[PDB]
Image (tube, rainbow over all chains, first blue to last red):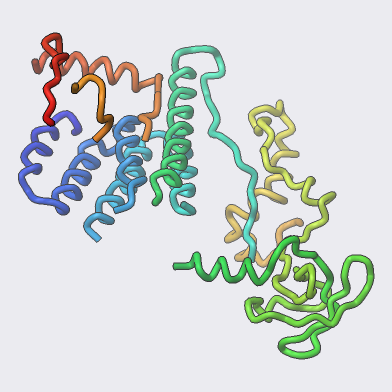
Length: 90
Length: 178
Length: 46
């Protein structure tokens, strides 16, 4: 249920970083579990692309969210395979 | 090991007919493609040790580096390498070369001036052979064959099923038709 | 005196399939959320 998590992230903004970033990323990912949102996967890829533990926890949850949102459809999973390989070798 | 270098292929679009569902599928594939492009374009740009070792190795190696054939291994730091023109040279094996791969008949990489062995060429595959490898898989799938069912079943049991479900053959005790 | 003298002292992927509509929808969500007296007589010291 990704239509009722914006307030959740707003509330989570209170907690201090870097755990705040990890919590926000994980909550956002679990909000759109299987929804196949291209924009949210794009934000997750942005998060993964930036290199800073907990900061690495952000990227780990971002990759897990990429998989979660991509699992909805066959095309999404097949393309996420290539994206995951690319980000593994890079 | 050098596992399979399977040909790359994009997923298949089912609608075929120019309906908006096909447009959505192609748009999703393009979105993931742009996704990968942006990610890998930011990686190097967004990117800001081993550099010292790499520089030392490359400065010792020098360029250009000749590719020759290793004829024999005399000592742990000496070998006889025959240059491409057929002339044999008693060159010195440098430290930064895994002695395990150094076997007679391998294509060794040599310094241009002193001819000292600096690396072993792994692939060195004949260019007339590397062309044969199928990189872009053809778009014609099984649904693109009318009938030829028995034939499809036989070919699958010979070349396709053994990889996917080798359990059946292993339990039955019969090596799949190769 | 000020006028003339001592001088000096990640691209968001287009994703037009979904991204353009998403941007317009976010714009809608935001909408619902919403020298002349220059010292030409520059003074100077000795």
